[PDB]
Structures are given as structure tokens and as C-alpha cells.
Image: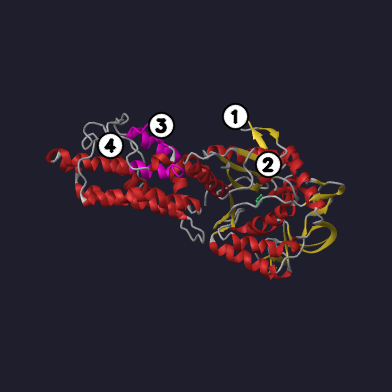
Amino acid sequence: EKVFFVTSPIYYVNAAPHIGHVYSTLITDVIGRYHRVKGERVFALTGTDEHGQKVAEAAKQKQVSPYDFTTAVAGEFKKCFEQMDYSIDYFIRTTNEQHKAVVKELWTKLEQKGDIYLGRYEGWYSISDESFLTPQNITDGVDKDGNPCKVSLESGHVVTWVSEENYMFRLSAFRERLLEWYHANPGCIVPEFRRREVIRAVEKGLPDLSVSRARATLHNWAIPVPGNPDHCVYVWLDALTNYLTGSRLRVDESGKEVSLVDDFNELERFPADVHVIGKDILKFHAIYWPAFLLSAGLPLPKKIVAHGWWTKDRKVFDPVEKAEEFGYDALKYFLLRESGFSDDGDYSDKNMIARLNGELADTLGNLVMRCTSAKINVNGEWPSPAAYTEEDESLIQLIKDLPGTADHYYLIPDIQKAIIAVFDVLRAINAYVTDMAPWKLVKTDPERLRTVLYITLEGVRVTTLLLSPILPRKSVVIFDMLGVPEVHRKGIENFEFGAVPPGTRLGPAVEGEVLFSKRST
Ligand code: MET
């Protein structure tokens, strides 16, 4: 058994954080959280990509020192992610001195294997993307305010010509082995249609990669190539290596580096089990990264997951201002429920209220109040169930089956599908509780109401446990209301139906207390 290692991308610090950095780190955070509720060892990583030309020129364009500028923005991200109530284990910055150490270690390995040579790169380059492009991937446009230019087909950003003596990685030598890797491990890229993409790109053919830049081009704002101060190491090799760095750093209780281990095995994190990325940075993680790792004889990641968003601004959301107006758990829910891999989601104020009210408030929120109500649940107690009718069983079967299926969805990973799976069982429970009319049974058939109440409660409990990674603060409130002991709030033991025994007492109530309160109509 290993440490389960989940990563977000590390974000260029040229601009403040926005929705999107937050979405990316949310997925990373939710996966991590789910494996922790399974009781696994987890290490989730996130952070900032602070070197290179893009960022240098961002710092120049605001007339501030890049040493001061990267630190400033980096702090804004940290402040944003802290406000966003994630459970990330470490925040990593490429300016960190221990990271620089690993880049040089990694570089030397790449060199010693005979995989790096001194060449030229003469071709197109998007600075905003820090991406080398061939002429098939650029086209005319006017991203220059006035004048007409050539622009990236991927991003749309301005591309410029570069003719440099650069250090070159033999990425071309790694084609057939990448191709083997993708095939032998067909889950290694998710979603499937982006795996299909990568394999087409790599089967067409791979050129060598320009892993360094002339020192003056970058404004000297990059790590020096070992043994050649005239050169700076390509920001993306620098960036990608954060995953290795992070996997080697002992971190103290309050979240600060203390050591850099020599051997990545010592901490047991590497390779990343899941690399959460945005669709715009697929090639770096799915082609370049593996090929680097294969060269140095390092273990390949286990899977790369590219969501449908961009990682870097395109085209109505301040993350924290929205979480403050609508709710932190509801926002995270909404973002996870609404956006799939091919995306096309609707994020209007209408739709957020639609789901807040319909799903969080009327499906989930409502069930909790019925099954803890003073009027229905008269003794504030988990009752022992009597005999089960076939309907009782039918619903119980769903609740028994839910953890297994929700678990597979969580492992794909597909947080959307998982949330759908849980709320399907939730929807069933409401249907069940309508049919059964407990409010009528308190008076007519006390013995029946026991069976029903028990099933509702245990239904609400398990759905809630599988929703914990999405609604972390709100699951805690639900459990307190239900009176679930702390030892039952976590661990696959407690995926089992009937793990909280009858006799358990509910938590105290407040005269007016609400779990999710509807938004205006
Ligand atoms: C190590 S992932 C690097 C991602 C890059 N900094 C970006 O913002 O897209």
C-alpha cells in the first residue's frame, strides 16, 4: 500500500486567482477527501508556477520586481485556497529552493542517459501558453490590440518566432514507448476521448523538445541549466517537476517544508495516482511528462484526468464572493454537479438557484428534517426496525448498492456521475417517504413507523457519507443532527448498511434551524 497522491496543476502567477484555478484545485481536493473518508493515506498537492517569460513579463508590465511579484500573487492564491476551505496537504512554489534542487537532479539524470543534446529550435512559440507550436497549429488573427498577427490554434494567444541554440530532449526517441504505455494502461488518461486524442498526436509523430532557453529571453527568471549558466531550464520541465518535488518533501503539522528526501520511496507518494489537469495542458502531462520520467527511469503516473475547463482565463465569477452570496458547500456542489468532461454547463444565477432549491434543499435538506423531526421521530432516537416489506427491501437494496457504484465513479474519477448516483438514491428515499406517509404512521402504526424511520435515517446517513467529499461542512451538520458517532463518519466499514445501531440518540435542535435555505423567487 502506498500514499494516495493527488495533484492539481500549479498555476501561473501573472494574474490573481479566479474561478478555474479554484475548480481545478476543487477536483483535486474532492478526490483527496474521498480517499481520506475511505481511511487511506492521502497526500494532495497544489501550488504556483512562478518562473519563466510569461510571469517575468507580467511582473515587468506592472513595474514590480519579479521576486516581490511572484510572492505577492502566490500569497493571494494561498489566501484564496485557504478561504475556499480545501484539505490540501501542501502548497508548492517553483521559486522554492528545494524544488530548484530537484529540477537540477532530474536534469542531470536526463543528461546522463544521453537524452539531452545541444541543438537549435527555430519555430513558433506562444508565450502566454509557454508552448512550442508547429505551423499547422497557428493561424492569422489580431490579438495585438490593433495590428494583425499569427495566433495559437489551441489558446488563441499571440505566437512569435524564435531562433535559439537550445538544449534539446530526445522526445522523438520515446514515441513507441509512450504508445505502448497508453495501450497497456487504457485508464491512464481520462476521459477516454482525450486518450484517443493523445494517441493520434503521438502516432502522427514526435519531434524533439526544447528544454532550455537563452538566458536573456526569460529575463533570467528561471532555474539555470546545470553546467551551462548561459541557459535556463524550460519553465514546463521546471513546472512538471513540482509533482516529484512535492512527493519528496517532509511537511510539518502547520504545512511547511522541513526536508527534501533523497529517495522518493522514503515518503511513499510518487508516482501521482491522479494528476488533475485542465484540457488546455494535456500534452505536457500526457506526452512530455511521461517521456521525461521514462528517460530518467522513474515510475509513470497512474492516471491523468483532464476536466473540461481551461486552466487559464478565457472570456462572471469571483469564487469567494459567490461562496459568500450562495454558500461554500453549495457552490462546490454546483460546480461539481454542473460540469462534465465535454462540459457545456449552464452557470447562471437561475440554474444555481434551481439546483440549490431542488437538489440541496428539497431532496437532501428536506429528508434530513423529516427523519429528525420532533413530530415524526418522536423519541429523537434511531428505532429498531420491525419486519421489512418488499418495498422496504427494494429501497434497502439501493442503499446497499450505492457505495460500490459511487466508489467506482469516484475512482474513474467522475465526481459528476458520483453526485448523480447518490442523489438518485436520495430521490428514491423521498418517493419512499411520500408513499409511506410517516406523519400518518406516528398515530396509526407505531410498529410500522419504526421500520420506515430506521430506513430513512440509514439512507440519509449513507448518502451523506458518500457526499462528504463534496459537502464537507454540511455533512458534519447532518451527522450531528442524526447523532452519528465520530468513529462512524469515515471508513469503508461504515459504508455498510446498519453500521450505526438503533438506540443512538439524535443531536440537539434550534427553533428555526435550517440546513440549506431556499433562494429568492
Ligand atoms: C505543473 S502544471 C503547470 C500549469 C501551468 N502553470 C498553467 O497555468 O497552465
Residue 473 lies in the magenta stretch: yes
Task: Point out the tag, 2 or 3, that comes first from the N-terminus.
Answer: 2
Measure the alpha-carbon separation of dots 4 and 1: 38 Å
**Amino acid type, mark 4:** Thr
Secondary structure, mark 3, is helix
Mark 3, residue position? 486
Which span is picked out in magenta? 460-489
- Left or right relative to 19: residue 259: right
Mark 4, residue position? 372
Asked whether mark 2 lies closer than 8 Å to ligand 1, one says no
Q: Residues within 10 Å of mark 2 (few under 14, many from 20)?
A: some
Q: Residues within 10 Å of mark 3 (few under 14, many from 20)?
A: few
Asked if residue 304 can be seen in this view, the reply is: yes
Secondary structure, mark 2, is helix
Q: Nearer the viewer, residue 97 or 102?
A: 102
Q: Nearer the viewer, residue 234 or 39?
A: 39
Mark 2, residue position? 264
Residue 247 screen position, x and y as percent: 65, 41
Mark 1, residue position? 253
Q: Is residue 503 above or below residue 363?
A: above
Measure the alpha-carbon separation of dots 1 and 2: 20 Å
Residue 348 lies in the magenta stretch: no
Question: What secondary structure predominates along the stretch shown in magenta?
Answer: helix
Residue visible at 29% across and 52% down in the picture: 428
Location of residue 306 (image quadrant): bottom right
Measure the alpha-carbon separation of dots 2 and 4: 49 Å
